Amino acid sequence: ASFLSSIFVPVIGWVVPIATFSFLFLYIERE
Amino acid sequence: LETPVNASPLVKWFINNLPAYRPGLTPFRRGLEVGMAHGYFLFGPFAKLGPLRDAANANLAGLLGAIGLVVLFTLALSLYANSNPPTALASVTVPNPPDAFQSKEGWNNFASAFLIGGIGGAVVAYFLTSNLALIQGLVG
Amino acid sequence: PPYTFRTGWALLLLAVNFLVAAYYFHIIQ
Amino acid sequence: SHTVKIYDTCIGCTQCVRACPTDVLEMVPWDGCKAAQVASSPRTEDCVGCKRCETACPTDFLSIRVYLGAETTRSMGLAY
Amino acid sequence: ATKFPKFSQDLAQDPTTRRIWYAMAMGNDFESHDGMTEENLYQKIFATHFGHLAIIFLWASSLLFHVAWQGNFEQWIKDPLHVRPIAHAIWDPHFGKPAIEAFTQAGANGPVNIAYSGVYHWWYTIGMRTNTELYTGSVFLLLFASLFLFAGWLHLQPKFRPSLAWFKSAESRLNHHLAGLFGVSSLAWAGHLIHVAIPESRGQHVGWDNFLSTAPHPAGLQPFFTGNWGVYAQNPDTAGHIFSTSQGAGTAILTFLGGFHPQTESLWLTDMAHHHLAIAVLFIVAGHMYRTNFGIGHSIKEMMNAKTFFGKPVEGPFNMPHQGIYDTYNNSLHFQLGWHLACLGVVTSWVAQHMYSLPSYAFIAKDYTTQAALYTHHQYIAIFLMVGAFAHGAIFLVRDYDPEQNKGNVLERVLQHKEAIISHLSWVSLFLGFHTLGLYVHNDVVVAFGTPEKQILIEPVFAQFIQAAHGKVLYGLDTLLSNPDSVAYTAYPNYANVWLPGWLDAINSGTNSLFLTIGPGDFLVHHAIALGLHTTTLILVKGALDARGSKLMPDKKDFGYAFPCDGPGRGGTCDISAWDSFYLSLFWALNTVGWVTFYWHWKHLGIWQGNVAQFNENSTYLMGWFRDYLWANSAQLINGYNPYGVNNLSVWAWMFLFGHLVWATGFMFLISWRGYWQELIETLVWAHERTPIANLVRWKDKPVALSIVQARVVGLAHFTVGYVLTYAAFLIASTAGKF
Amino acid sequence: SISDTQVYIALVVALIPGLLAWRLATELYK
Ligand code: CLA
Ligand code: CLA
Ligand code: CLA
Ligand code: CLA
Ligand SMILES: CC1=C(/C=C/C(C)=C/C=C/C(C)=C/C=C/C=C(C)/C=C/C=C(C)/C=C/C2=C(C)CCCC2(C)C)C(C)(C)CCC1
Ligand SMILES: CC1=C(/C=C/C(C)=C/C=C/C(C)=C/C=C/C=C(C)/C=C/C=C(C)/C=C/C2=C(C)CCCC2(C)C)C(C)(C)CCC1
Ligand code: SF4
Ligand code: SF4
């Protein structure tokens, strides 16, 4: 099942930092 | 009096967490864990010590014996229930009864869940001892 | 004062320094 | 802001008041020293942590001391 | 005016971008948080310690799973001496087609990374044979790491949350951790070797299914209880034992040959079994020493405060005042953390010193690059653990230290004569450096002038002796286990040197790293190492002892541990704080471990290639280091990619250049300091409010330059990462390109 | 190597520490 690399690596490469940075930027800039 | 056996906090924490005494439980829930526990080990001395313990149906000799004696206990629970039982005691390690063991209605709920759990505890012990080489291939 | 407890252990350790050199100089074998 | 502690060892030299560029320091009368005045810091929300006031003090060791604390806009020295 | 960071109101009221950066470097500092009390501190550190513990098991499970699913472990069993291991596989979309063909290696379908961490040798030694045991141990560590993630959550709930007196019960940790964590676990691993790993070493499969049926010994635990323990040391694995087969096998489970297995050139598994069994008995006995609630045992607070040696009044133990040290170790957490990093830092290098000379893993002495990486790894780990020992020891003296509780004791007497410690440390650093650099430059000029016989070459005659006092005939000193007439050789009253015939076979062969032959090139580098240890200690001790103030600046304790300076006054005070003496030392600590690992690597490149004469001639003068090691070995590396093509070294050729760039970037934060850059950002703030379309958007946090203490962190971070990655790309590919 | 089935068991079992790590890291405060 070597096709899981095609679906975990782009999520951790792209989706994981986009979801993390967009959470943290809205959390540090929160009155 | 008071000793490090009846009152050490390791033992007070233990006895107050058995399902006979754990706070906030339906009496069906109390007899469910008491039943599954006592139905699990009582598969033991019938299967490997019984009269047909060398035959190919050795574990089935232990299953019908252990189920058939959970049914005997469940009668004795319902015999103790229907006899207008006296209120339970309060020792130095357990300061209060679990409040479901003074009504006739509460022992009847305790009696049924022993039967539901005691049969299921014996079946899973029949499942695990007949499938030893199954588990040790799922492990190695 | 003549430091007895200090010099007592320094002469013990220096006696270990001289003992190992006796093996290295073949004085003791 | 920062924290400006002034101990009781100074002589009223008025070198620290004439060196703090945001004018935090001022002289108040005080019957202790020979010049009969001690430095005081009543406006420490304006202090920028420059430590020009510690450089100009004669006494050994320093009678004035700047403790660097939480940095707001006035103490960062930001024109924006 | 935001609510981030939660742990500080002084940082959360910062309008600049300093708010963002100081949240990161004060986040795990639990002691400086807002409103943090004493018992809330320990209860939060204890549950955090379940968090770091469960990272370790989740880390070690990915080593098992990525090998079982993507590596060639079952193909590596058949021939471990030529089959080249596999760590994981590459899914890189940015690869070109000649860079998929170059990394399709070791007999695999796709691009794979050759494992240079040696975990196939450790798993093959301890009995694991197929890819299913690797997967089973992987899934077990998923559950075993979740058992600690639940435990840290459980011990933060209010009636499951431990009290303060539970943490400061120090005599009960020492009984449970020595007997249980050290002793039972050494006993359990001896049970794992004897039941499983030693029978797996003889071609005899023992798994979870049949370990209750099969016995490790045909005698079978009857000679244990009767006292006939010599039955366990019957016929061992012979000198023709082919590993993991039944040829030349034995029945013994606890044996004491000493030396190495003749094929794998590792330690005998029967020797390790009697080792961890004997370690286990020495620790369970050691764990029944200190006083707990059972009214028996030694009491450490009474051992410190004792003043009477058999009626004679003394100042304390060894007539030295150790009173109040129990209330100094146990009350402070930085004294504990500063202490135990020194303890863990000693053993970490001590691991590395004994794993190249005494290999304990099957076929690891012949897989070279896995052995060159494991030495250099645990040496650099030992570097940071020793620098942080003095670092967290110096946070103790600023923050936690109390001179009244510690009055008159041995830790007070060090702070009195601290100018005598730093002076004689400054002497040895200069006494070595003036005369070690002097003899390299002497040998450099002398060889350059074509007359190399005028070199000053010193035989290391004090370490020549120790190797001959351990049994090396090669020098002819004829003492002490090399003298066969010696009292130490024969063990005169009892003659019980069982280890000694197997030890002298190992030390007298020229086919291992056991007590390598040393010469005049090894004289100068051990005195160059001693230059690096006494000088790194000089910076760290002087920053520890002067952490509470001195002549140029008294009351440095009022300013905390990390503050920039005290201004340009008094001549200026740049890098005056106790943090700044942590800072200067990590240049030396990375330097010194360079010297100990340039010298490790180049002595073994002569052993592995059969050319011992290249090192012994050329390591006396500093061109031979520069030419025959740095220049000559980086030819396979730098040709990892050229205009002709690529090969499998092109990552290490790319990481080598990457390391030279991160290293050089860190100079920018150190040569140039802050006030240049705040006057540069104030022109970018101007030209953003004036640009007509781009001033629709605007910052929430005002841009300021990095603070003075911050870009010494950021400067040291680019320096250290680039120092590691440069050598780690040179260490691997110069060894894995030559074998 | 290991079978294609066994990889999915390892992923589902890995949600059990993934859930518990989210519980611990939020019990340690925000
Ligand atoms: C921390 C441990 C760790 C690390 C660094 C890696 C590293 C890698 N894995 Mg792997 N993996 C691990 C544990 C680990 N694995 C475990 C336990 C499992 C079983 C569930 C897997 C299952 C797995 C699969 C199925 C695949 C990878 C793949 C990969 C590669 C690409 C990264 C990726 O997509 O992640 C994938 C990540 C996951 C599937 C889930 C992560 C599971 C661990 C337990 C999370 C650890 C989080 C960490 C502790 C949080 C701390 C962050 C830190 C910065 C503070 C890379 C070699 C891919 C690959 O080989 O591409 C070629 C791929 O297809 N991994
Ligand atoms: C017998 C009972 C027992 C046991 C097993 C433990 C075990 C542990 N306690 Mg502990 N504890 C106990 C009783 C016990 N405690 C009691 C009674 C108290 C109260 C008085 C405490 C109070 C306490 C506190 C307050 C803390 C612990 C912590 C820990 C953990 C230490 C960190 C760790 O995992 O290192 C594991 C270390 C080893 C397995 C030994 C390593 C030996 C050296 C360093 C290396 C030797 C290995 C060798 C070279 C070979 C390795 C090679 C191989 C890896 C390839 C560990 C799980 C800490 C922790 O992390 O909390 C979770 C912590 O903060 N304990
Ligand atoms: C188990 C050991 C241990 C423990 C528990 C601690 C715990 C602590 N230390 Mg300590 N320390 C340690 C080891 C340890 N340290 C070691 C080994 C050293 C020597 C290097 C130090 C040096 C040290 C100093 C000098 C200081 C501390 C401080 C602290 C406290 C706060 C930490 C903090 O703010 O984190 C914040 C974390 C960071 C800022 C992390 C940034 C650094 C990361 C690791 C860089 C990584 C680079 C990058 C990811 C690489 C990518 C590569 C890629 C490009 C290819 C805390 C009590 C500080 C304090 O004030 O104490 C109260 C403090 O001043 N420690
Ligand atoms: C042949 C070339 C050569 C050269 C160029 C040097 C050059 C140097 N040596 Mg060196 N040395 C050499 C050979 C050489 N050495 C040899 C063969 C020996 C073995 C005996 C030594 C032993 C030696 C010692 C023991 C010391 C030096 C020191 C020095 C430095 C200052 C010397 C001086 O006069 O300062 C001017 C002199 C003074 C400022 C005060 C006098 C200090 C003298 C050197 C010590 C004598 C005091 C006492 C009698 C002995 C002290 C006990 C000692 C045995 C441990 C200087 C760089 C010193 C050093 O490294 O300081 C950092 C130092 O302490 N050297
Ligand atoms: C060791 C020890 C101990 C312990 C002991 C005991 C107590 C044991 C027991 C054990 C047991 C005795 C167990 C049991 C278990 C059980 C189980 C595990 C079961 C399961 C079951 C199931 C799962 C079932 C289910 C079901 C039902 C319920 C119904 C329907 C059907 C079915 C089947 C589904 C003590 C602490 C004292 C002390 C120390 C040591
Ligand atoms: C050879 C040999 C031997 C011997 C050995 C020995 C004797 C060893 C030694 C060892 C040692 C001798 C070690 C040591 C080490 C040390 C160190 C490592 C230190 C460190 C420290 C620290 C770091 C500290 C810290 C601190 C500070 C800084 C401040 C205050 C606080 C504190 C204290 C914490 C024997 C006989 C056995 C056998 C044979 C061989
Ligand atoms: S603090 Fe310094 S400048 Fe101010 S009065 Fe005292 S001595 Fe003068
Ligand atoms: S912070 Fe120092 S330099 Fe600045 S105004 Fe105050 S006393 Fe003067």
Image (spheres, grey):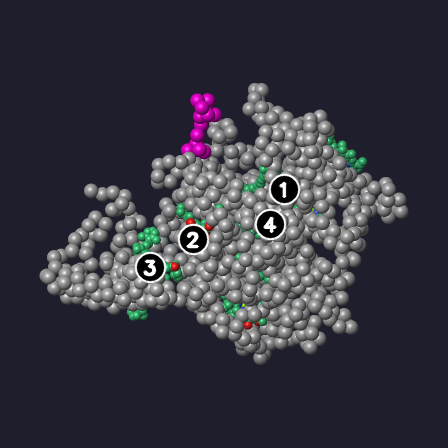
Furthest-top residue in this view:
C1
Q: Which residues are magenta?
A: E302-314
Residue E490 against residue E61 in the figure, above or below: above
Q: Between residues E656 and E681, which one lies in front from this camera angle? A: E656
Task: Decide which of tag 2 and tag 1 comes sooner along the chain.
Answer: 2
Q: Give the alpha-carbon distance from disc 4 to disc 1, as whole Å.
A: 51 Å
Do pointers 3 and 4 mark residues of a single chain? no
Pointer 3 residue:
B48
Mark 1 is surrounded, within 10 Å at the Cα level, by few (under 14), some (14 to 19) or many (20 or more) other residues, namely: many
Secondary structure beneath dot 3 equals loop
Pointer 2 residue:
E46
Furthest-right residue in this view:
E450
Furthest-left residue in this view:
B84
Q: Give the alpha-carbon distance from disc 2 to disc 1, as whole Å.
A: 34 Å
For the C terminus of chain E, which image quadrant? bottom right
Do pointers 4 and 2 mark residues of a single chain? yes
Pointer 1 residue:
E538
Q: Residue at x 60, y 33 (%)?
A: E495
Q: Residue at x 74, y 34 (%)?
A: E477
What type is the residue that disc 4 sits on?
A: Asp
Magenta span has E305?
yes
Indicate the position of residue C6 as horizontal and vertical percent values.
Answer: 57, 25
Mark 4 is surrounded, within 10 Å at the Cα level, by few (under 14), some (14 to 19) or many (20 or more) other residues, namely: many
Q: Give the alpha-carbon distance from disc 2 to disc 3, as whole Å.
A: 46 Å
Secondary structure beneath dot 1 equals helix
